[PDB]
Every structure is written in C-alpha cells, then in structure tokens.
Image: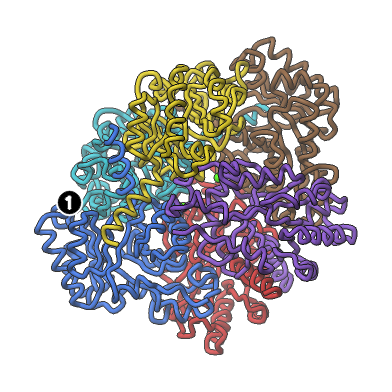
Chain colours: A yellow, B blue, C red, D cyan, E purple, F brown
Amino acid sequence: MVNTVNYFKQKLKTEQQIGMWVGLADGYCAEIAANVGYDWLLIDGEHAPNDVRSILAQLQSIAAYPSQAVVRPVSGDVPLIKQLLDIGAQTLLIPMVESAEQAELMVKATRYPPEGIRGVGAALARASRWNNISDYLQTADEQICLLVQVESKKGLDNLDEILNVDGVDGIFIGPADLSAALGYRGNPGHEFVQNIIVQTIQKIRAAGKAAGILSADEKLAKQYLELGTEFVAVGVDTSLLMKSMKQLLSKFK
Amino acid sequence: MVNTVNYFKQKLKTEQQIGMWVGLADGYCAEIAANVGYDWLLIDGEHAPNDVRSILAQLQSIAAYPSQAVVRPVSGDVPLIKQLLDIGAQTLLIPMVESAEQAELMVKATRYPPEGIRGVGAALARASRWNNISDYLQTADEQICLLVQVESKKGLDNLDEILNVDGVDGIFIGPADLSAALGYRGNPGHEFVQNIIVQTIQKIRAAGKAAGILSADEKLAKQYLELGTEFVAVGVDTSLLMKSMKQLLSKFK
Amino acid sequence: MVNTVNYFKQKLKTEQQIGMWVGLADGYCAEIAANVGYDWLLIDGEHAPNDVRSILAQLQSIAAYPSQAVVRPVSGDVPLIKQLLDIGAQTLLIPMVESAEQAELMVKATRYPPEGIRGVGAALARASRWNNISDYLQTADEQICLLVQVESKKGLDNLDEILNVDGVDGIFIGPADLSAALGYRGNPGHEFVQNIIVQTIQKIRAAGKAAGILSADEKLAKQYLELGTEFVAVGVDTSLLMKSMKQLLSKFK
Amino acid sequence: MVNTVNYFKQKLKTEQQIGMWVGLADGYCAEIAANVGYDWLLIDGEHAPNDVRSILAQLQSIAAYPSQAVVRPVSGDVPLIKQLLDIGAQTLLIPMVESAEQAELMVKATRYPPEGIRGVGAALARASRWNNISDYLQTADEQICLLVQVESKKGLDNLDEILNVDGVDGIFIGPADLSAALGYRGNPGHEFVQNIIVQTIQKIRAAGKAAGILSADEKLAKQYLELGTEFVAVGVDTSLLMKSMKQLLSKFK
Amino acid sequence: MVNTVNYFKQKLKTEQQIGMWVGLADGYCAEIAANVGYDWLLIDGEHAPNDVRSILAQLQSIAAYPSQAVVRPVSGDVPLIKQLLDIGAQTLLIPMVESAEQAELMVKATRYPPEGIRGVGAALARASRWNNISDYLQTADEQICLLVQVESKKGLDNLDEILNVDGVDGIFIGPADLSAALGYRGNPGHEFVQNIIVQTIQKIRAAGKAAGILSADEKLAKQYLELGTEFVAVGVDTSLLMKSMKQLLSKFK
Amino acid sequence: MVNTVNYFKQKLKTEQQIGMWVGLADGYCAEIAANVGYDWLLIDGEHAPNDVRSILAQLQSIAAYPSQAVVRPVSGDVPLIKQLLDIGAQTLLIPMVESAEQAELMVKATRYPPEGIRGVGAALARASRWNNISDYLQTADEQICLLVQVESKKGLDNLDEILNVDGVDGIFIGPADLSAALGYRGNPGHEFVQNIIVQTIQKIRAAGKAAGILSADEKLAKQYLELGTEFVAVGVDTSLLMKSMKQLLSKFK
Ligand SMILES: [Ca+2]
Ligand SMILES: [Ca+2]
C-alpha cells in the first residue's frame, strides 16, 4: 500500500476548498456529513466532546468518502498531536498559536526525528495501516499538513513571524475567539473586526501560505472566497441540526 | 417521588402534538432535538441503530426537557417491551400490528400481572427510580401509553378489530411501509394511498382512539392536522441534518 | 488449559450460597460487588439495562475474584442463551419458565449437539478461551448449570413436571413476579404468598433440585436459609446504593 | 449517489472468493482485517459478542476497503435481519436454516413489500445513505445477497427443497455445527463427515447455487476450492491472534 | 432559553449545601445519586475513571434533577477546563492549587476574553445549548462558579494570597491529600491535622469566601457544619456501595 | 485484602520476563493476549488509541490471569500517572525520559506525600479496591514499579544521571525512536545503532537497574536475552494479527 495521499494539502495550492465543521462527536454523524460532498470536514477536538478514540471512529467513517478530514486538537499539546497523527489524522488545525517559537514546535511535533519530535510507533498505528504501508516512516512527513489558528491579540502581534515558519501550511482565522479577543465577543460582524480579518487574510496569502476561515454567514463566506481564501468552512453540523429542527417546528408552533 | 406524569398520553384527548423523529441514535443528538420544543420525540428502535442501552442514554438526555419521549421497539416483542418499560419509556409505538389478538398481547405486555404480563423488577428499574417512586407497582399502568402501527394490508383488513382493543390508545400510520404494502413503494403521495390514509384516520378517530402519522411534507402534515390527527411527526433528524448540509453546500458547490 | 470449574454448580449439593443481585449494568460496578465475597453474583439481563456486550464486560471484571457469575437472560430465547454461553456464562437463570416442555428446551439450549441444540463456535468464544481450552467441546456441558424461575400460576401449575426435567439443576422463586401473579403485586409479605413459597421450596428440595430465592428482608432470607434453600440472594446493588445514599442524606436533611 | 454495488454477489457466478472470519467484534480490529485483501470478511453476529451497533462500526471501518462484508446474524430473526439491512449489510449468512419454508421466509425478510416483508425506513438508514441514494427503494433488492447455513440433520434432510428456493444465492456448510450434529463434535476431519460435506457441495453447485465453507485447515480449504466451492473462508481472526501469540511465546517459553 | 441558573453558586452565600461524591463514573450511577436529593453532586475527574465524554453523560443524567453538578478536573489544565465548561459544567473544583498566580490563571480559564482566556465555541457547546441560549456569550461568566482545593503545605503557605484572588468563590479542603501532605497519610483524624483544618476554614470564611470539605465521618461532618462550612460532602458513592454490600454479607457470612 | 503483589517488580531481580505489546486497545483483545502465558503485557497508552477508561477495561480483563500488566502513558504527565495508578496499574513505562530531573519527578509522581506527589484518593480507586485493601495508603508504594524509556540523544547524554536516580527500577530501550533519533529511522538493524543499544544495556545492568527492550526479530530478542536483559517484549498484537492474516491469504492469493 502507498501512504494515503493528502488531497487537502495539495489542494491548498490549486483550489478553494469548502468545509463543514463536525462537532456531533460521533462516527455515525461524521458519516452523514461525509456523504454530502464537502472538500473537508473539521473534526473538532477543541469545542466538541471528542477524545482520541471518538476522533478515530470519525476518521474510519469518513475514510470511505472523498471528503478530507482535518482534526483540531484541544491545544498544541505535543503528545496529543503524536496520538492524532498515529490514528491517521493527516491534517491538523492547532488552536491558539501565538508565536513563531510555538509554531516551529508544532511543525516539529508533526515530523519524525531526527528533523522533528513525532514519537515513532508505526507497527501500532492506523497511520501506517500497522506497517501495511511498507515505507511509512520514510513517506509520512510528505502527506502531513499543519494549520495553525491565530485567535488572540498576541497571535496578531506575531503574525509576520508565524508566517515565516517553514512547515506552517496555513493560518486559519476563527472570527469567534478573534472578535472576543478584540472586545466584540459574539459580534464578529463589526467593521473593526472585519477590517482586521481581511488584512490578516491578505498578509497570510502575501507570505505564500493558505488562509482559512469559518463563517455560517453566506455573504461573509462568499466575500472571503472572493479574496482567494483557500479553505473556507461554511457551516457547523450542530448549528444546522438545531436550526433545521427549530425552523421546521416554527411552521407548526 | 410521585410517578412521572405522561403528558403525551393526557394530551391525546386535549390537543394536537407535533413530533420529531429521533434516529441519530445518540444521547448527545437526542439532547439537541430535546431543546427545540417538539411536543414528542420518537426514539426509533426499529429503523435507527439503537439498543436498550442507547435508548436509555436518550431517555436520560431528553428527561431534563419538556418534550415527551415515545420509543418504537424493533417489533412487538414481549421481553423487549418489558426492557424498554423498565428503563422508563412511558409511551411505546409498536410496529407491524396486524390483528386484535396481537394488539391485546401488546396491551398485556405493558401491564403488570395479574391483569397483564409485564415482568416485575421495580427495585432495578429507572422506571420506579429504583423504588424512589414508592407506589410504582400500584401507579405504573396509569402513565403507560400504547400506540400501534398499521402498515400492511392485513392490518387494514383488521383495523376495526384493532380499534375495539381496550388499551390501544392510538394507531399510527407510517405512509412508507403502507405505500410499499399497497404497491407504491417510495410514492406515498399517490391518490390511491392518500384516500386510504384519510379513511383510516377518520375510522381511528370515529372509534375514540388517537390517530398519528409522520410526513416531512409540510402540505400533507398540515392536511393531516386539519383532519384532527392527534400526534403528527413533521420531520426526521437524519433527514434534516443531511438536507441542511446538502442545501448549504449547493450555495458554494 | 482445563475448562473453568463451575463451583456454583458443585456447591448446589454441598452448601448454601449467598448471592448479590448485580443490576448496575457496568464492568466497574460488577468489580466492586466482586470484591465483597458473595458466593454468587446475578448479572441481570432481564431487569437491568444489559446486552451481551455489557454482560461480557461484567464477566471479565468478576473473573479475577472467587464470586461465581450467574446470568439471567431477558427470556428463554435459544439464540440469546447460545450467545451468553459463548461469552463464558456457565450458570444461567431462565425467567418465566412455565412447562416441562419449555424446561426441556432450555436444557437442550445449554448442551451441544447431538444431545442438545447449543450452536458450535468454540474457535470464537471466550467460553473455550478461543480453543486455549483444548477439549472444550468434550468438557463444556459438565460445567454448565441451568436454573429456571417459576414466577406465574402456570409455572406453579406445572411445578412437579418441571421438577422431573433432567438437567434443570435448580428452581429459583422470585417473590416479585409471583406475588404479582397471585394478586398481591408489591406485597410478597402476605401469608397467602409466603405459604406458597415455603411449600414450593419444600417440593423443589424433595425432588432433589436446588431451591433459590431473593429477599432483601433479612428475616425472610434467614427463614429461607433455615428451610435449607441452596441459593439465596440477600440484596440488590441498585437498592443498596440508593438506600445507603438516602439514609446518609437523612442524617443532615 | 448510486447504491453500493454488491461485488460479493456478482463474484458468486464469476470467481472463487477467499474469506476471513471477523469475530474480534471491534471496528479497529475489523479495519486491520480489511487491509489484508480478503475477497470477503464475515462479521459474526452469532458466535462473537456483536450487536447491531458493533456491526455498524465494523461496516463503517471496512467500507473504505475493497473487502466485501458478509454479516451472520445470531438467528433467522426477521426484525434483526431488517436492522442489519438498514445499517447497510448487503450480504447476510443466516444460521441454522432447516426447511424450504424457513428459507423462503429469509428471502422475503430481505425484500421490500409488496414482494417481501423488509420494513421500509430509508430516510433513517445508512443502507440508503439517509436517502442520498435517491432510487434506493427501487434498486435495493438487486444488491442484496442471501446465504443460508445448513448445519443440522434436518437441514440435510431438506437440502433439495432449500436448493429450489428462488432468492437463496448460496448455501454455506459450517463443519463445526455439522460434525457435531452428525455425532463427531470437534472432529469434522472424519471421512463420514467429509463425504457428506463433498456430496452437499456437489448438490449445491448442481442446483446452480453458490457453495460456501470455512476451514482453517489449508489442505481441506484447497480441496474445497478444487471442487469449485464459490466462497471459502480460510481462517478466523481470534484463532490467528491466539495461535500467532502462542507460537511466538513457545520460541522463548 | 435563558442560561441555566447556577443555584450552587447562589447558595454559597445563603445556606449550607450537603454533597455526595460521584466516582462510579457512569451516567446510570450518576442518575441514581441524582434522585436522592443532595444539594450538590461532585463528578470526580481526578480520582475516578472519567474523561470529558463520561462527565458529559453524567451531566445529562443529573440535569433532569434539582441536585447541582460540580466537576473536579484531573488538574488545573486550562484546555481541559475549556472542555468541561463547554459540555456545560457550571461549577469546577480545581485540585492542587498552591499560589495566587495559579488561582488567578484558573479564574481567567473560566472567563471569556477579553477578561479571561476561555476558548470561544458557543455554536458547538451544550453550555450554550448550541446557541439556543441566545445571549450565552454575554451571560455565561455570571453562572460560572470556581472552587479551588488547598491540599499541600505550599497551598497552606499561600492561603491568604489565594483568598485575596477575586473570582475564587470557594476553597475546598480535602483531608486525604492534606493529612498525607502533613505526614499523617490515611489518618486525617489526628488533632494536629484537625486544628489546621479548623483554622483554614476560619480563615476562608473570614476572607468572605465559601469553605468546603469532604468527610464520611458523621461527627466530623456535623462539626464542620457547626463552624458554618458552606459546602460539605458527607459521603462517596463507591464507599457507600462497597460498605453497604459488606455490611449485608456479614449478616450471613 | 492484602495489596496485589507486583510479581513483575520482584522478577526484575530473579529472572528474565518475556513480554507482549498490547495495542489492540480493547478489553476483549487484552484478554486473548492474557491467555497465552506472557510474563508481562504492555498496555500501550502512547502509540495505541487508549485512554484511562480503555486501559481500565484491559486491566480488568488481564487481572484474572497470571500475566503482569505494564502501562505506557502517552507522556510523563504527573496527573495522567496519578490516574493510571488509581485504576490499579502497578508498573508504568514512561516514554521520552531525558534527564535525572525528569526521572526524579516520575519517581515522586508514583509515591504518596510526603515523600512523593501522587494525589490521594483511595476511597475511589480500584488500586485500593475502594478501601477493601485496608492498609493501601501504607503499602501502595512497595508494589509500584517505575520504568523509563531512553529514546533520544539527550536521554543517552543523561544515561549515567538517570541511572543514579533511586526509584527508577528499569530503563527500557525502544529501538524505533532511538534508531530514528540517531538518523536511521526505520532501520534499527544498523551496527551503529546496535552497538549503542548493547553498550546502553551493559551500563543499565552495571548500575543495578533492570534493562528492557522490544524486538519482533527473534535473533535480536535472543541476543538481548543472552546479554541478561531483564524484560524483553518479543512481539506486538497488532503486528501478529496483521502478519498472520497476510501470510494466510498468501497461500490462496
Ligand atoms: Ca473515552
Ligand atoms: Ca450495545
């Protein structure tokens, strides 16, 4: 078997990928999402009740389908990154990255020694298909994609430095934490926040990195796609489920 | 503690209850549904991957919310009915009921001896809250509601007889199995099927029993509510999740 | 490896075994109960929210401890009995046994062909420890113990017939279903019910079979032990947990 | 989406398919087995500790791989068959089939009304991918494959009658139950048993049905393949795990 | 929906709240404990085998009942605190707090930016009921309650400094870790230890914070209540289950 | 009850113990491995998809069998070590230990105050069998065994310093991470790497500590046993399963 090709990673340089946030934290819900045809599915280990084993179950469901999996761990924790890579997550979105130093450590956490600090356990891991991918330890690094989130004043204060870190493939901007960090908690729609988001996306793309964002607002999503944003999540499973059920009940109250 | 009051059962004689089909088979998804404000939630043990333990998890989630739980077991299996009552399901929807004899057996399956054949295990059961409901074995039968589904030619051929069974509180008509039994599999919208559904609802209400139905079609749902149908399910969680995600992706293809 | 000796089965003829009801339906709770020193633990598949997989987890917990496991399936279902024997349950308590014809079928359900109808699948089963017990298909039947419950008027109407079935090792009387069946639901304490229980125990022992019963009432339990009742369960984990927490809160209200 | 093509079913008429028994009852173990390259994987609901939900997880794992899933339910239970088809099992192996009448009922259990008695619930089912397979209710029957097991003297006494049942695609012979039924429990190797197996395979293929068998004995397996047996399982995951670990320890004792 | 009112937090200033430790690590066991009537239930993520998902299940169980949930995470880990607040835990008990600096970080961990460092993910969280609590991001901080444990000499050496931290609502003293830290491991009953506990409770209440403690000793528990201690846990589910089962067996040996 | 004797710990000074790696992450698979007769089983929390709850299930499975359990946590995390000791893991293998300062912290993490920093919670823990081991807080430390892994240049740079830490019972060398760290990723077989392994084993034994290693290569494993290596793991469950299934399929292609 040749290593699973990371089409998400390749597509960062060739197209704009449309994404769905997967927070229902369940192999069955992840499979329903995997049937729709999103370019990428964000399995949320930070804001949904997931652990290594529930994320594994969702990778297995989604694996039969074209949609590429991206895993957001709870934090840039090196051992947890080691766990998620070995279960076969090929793209990670690291929350709350605030310095070049922290971004380089995340690069190392995703690469085998001697170049990085990823723990070696290929015989045991879905990632190597238990060594059925015969050359895994030689070929793994090529198909790993590292994304970091900038979501604080300190991250924005270190944006140019993070953007010069080799091995950061993309910077994702989450309007929720960023709006809140800027003193507009719950109101990312403010001009002050939007101007900072647009400038940030411009700087990201100017430095040759992929820019990413989430917006459930169709107008803002299409605006971010007009700027060339490479990976745009356009909704959240929990929100779509809740709103579709509320909208239906309102027709009957 | 007094026994949990079955408001679904009481409401069969006082209003028209709007329902959501719960087939995501998960305590977390059941809780999202429980927040919307449906009158009733159908926990589907027949067509969703549920077992006694996953149904228990969904009863526990939903229990904090006003929405009344209805459990559809996989079949009119007496021991399985015993299990679902002891985990605290107070309303059951029995699929594929086709005779007075089978309907009376389902009544007995829901009532303690000597009047019925429900196995006695109150010390162990969430239903008695492990005997924290001190009078449970005296008061349980009052708050149990039995619904049966008519979904075959044989059931329609035995409708008058089922409708004279004391302890059948309601007859639910599932257009899917009924359309299929009538040779219009996948097309319940045919006039031949709809005329049979309307006549069936009329006969059900004429015999003093509650009529129920499911339709994701808003026009048919409101038509069934205009006829006085007592319990109408207006959608399905799996369908709302899939369609909301497909509709959103179509705005971006 | 030699097959696990069924000490419960042997002790039916040499001593009186003290039992605890396990309805907390969980490997971790079953292990707590396993530490106490009960002669037997009844893993309740009829009145607690258990399936084959949760019962297997409880057998694995308990296996490190001297306490012998007895499993009560939801009903005398031949395929379910097959499942529970293959996960390694060596003693079964069959609910709701009402005829010699039904007792004989339960005997066959527990014995391999050609003498019985137990499905053969030893390579796969914990019961054979996946063929690490090399002679399992030759030795299995010797260490299987079959108990049946008489809990209905019809059972009591067929008691002499059930007691002449070879391979029924014991008859358990559950006062809850029996009291209910006799029109004293929730009050097994009545003289009418108790006289029937005592006579029933006497007839069971007179026919050379083991008698069993459950009572959380210390006085009744010691009374049943004075009659020579071979297997006596003296409490229920769910009840002890609830009562201990209630008594404790009462000291501080 | 078009319905998943049942390649196992097609190959019954075009090649000889090599199978692995999957009784580790686990999505993770099922995925390891799925990477090997077996033509078919037998998810054992009869002799391994599986339920609908654990079988769903194993289907989801295996779905990303070419290996075709075959599910053996605990028994020819019509409601359980309904449940396994809806989670998306396209091939079923029914244990303990003993008459044409029982085989015909299993055929109907797998087909929608009006031809069959399969309960209709496509909106909810992974089988229809929650109606993302738009024609599912029209196209589903064509990709369903029904195998039955003959494992008793009564089955052998009804073999010609079972073989004339339209819609039985295959008869599988399990030497374990059959050897036991013939009074050679745990010694299927006996000439008396093997002559019966060979004759049975010849009769099955003579009637234009697929023959199937399991043998962990390489010689017997290759013999059955020389007879033209269409589906041959050649080992069992539990057995290969235990034996591989025992062989390794023996090199070091 | 308005945000769940944190009655535990309000009662810290108006009454003395009686608590039960919940370490059976199970939604079913948590629900049994929830029926008793304790003012608060301590879901122990530090000393019972719990993770985010098992704590969520226990929150869902308990939610239908008046008893207030308090969650003890394994350590003052900011990302884990983020995870427990989002699943909807409104009161946290932080183990092993030893400095004002650490207590201030725990305060911030529980509050949204710009005041605190709690990660923003309201669309996904049971805490916001998936934004069905429409003002959640504005109202969430008011219903969050932060308790810290002082259980080391260093903590006692920093007690006045921890007590001056705005946003620490309560200091809990666990005699087990504190007795051990003082060189009396497993004998918190010693006068040297008790004088320290009494003095500590007096200092905590003198600084206008709530004092808390656990003791299974009724006399010590009632003594701590006579001192005005605001939250007193009076037993542990694991201990009451084991002891109740041991006491019962001893009546029969 | 007396505390469980750690035979693994005792045997470090009296014999050479043969080990199997358990990465199938499942109570049912851990029990199959437990039947074989390995001296020790390594429950891998670093490279297999395990959490505290799945490790507890595997400890419960294995506990019925003579094989001693060793747990490898994901990292030398003090709170996680606390969790794993409380579920009853008596031998820990700490990955990625690189200094005497880190080894000493791991020693303290495994010992109660005042000598160590292990959090006290014996009422709640399987480790004390919920205080059924009456003297647990006095006797626990004697039966705890601490192993550390040297797997980096920095570890080898600190080997003499780590080897002088009292309370480090053993140093395990994992050829995978070490080979990788040395610039021979995936080829531990190189003379440069092997010479370092042999010298390392010699230095470990010269300092009075137990040496450990894993090799699936029979020749290397016997070589390590001839040097007197005290604990040698000779295979990996995931690898044996995959290889046994691959070899078997190869006979029939
Ligand atoms: Ca978990
Ligand atoms: Ca289950």
Residue F228 higher or lower than E73, as above or below: above
Q: Which residue is tagged 1? A: B185
Inspect this view and state whether residue C168 appears.
yes
Position above or below: A226 against B202 = above
Outermost residue on the left side: it is B191
Q: How many marks?
A: 1
Alpha-carbon neighbours of circle 1 within 10 Å: few (<14), some, or many (≥20)? some
Above or below for E199 versus D37: below
Q: Quadrant of residue F29?
A: top right
Q: Which one is in front, F128 or A160?
A: A160
**Residue E51: % across, % down:** 59, 47
Residue F139 appears left or right of C30: right
Q: Secondary structure at mark 1?
A: loop
* Residue F185, position as x, y percentages in the image: 60, 16
Q: Is mark 1 within 8 Å of ligand 2?
A: no
Report the residue at 54% width, 21% height from top: A160
Provide residue C199's location: percent of width, then percent of height. 55, 84
| Residue at 78 percent of width and 46 percent of height | F5
Q: Closer to the camera, D39 or A212?
A: A212
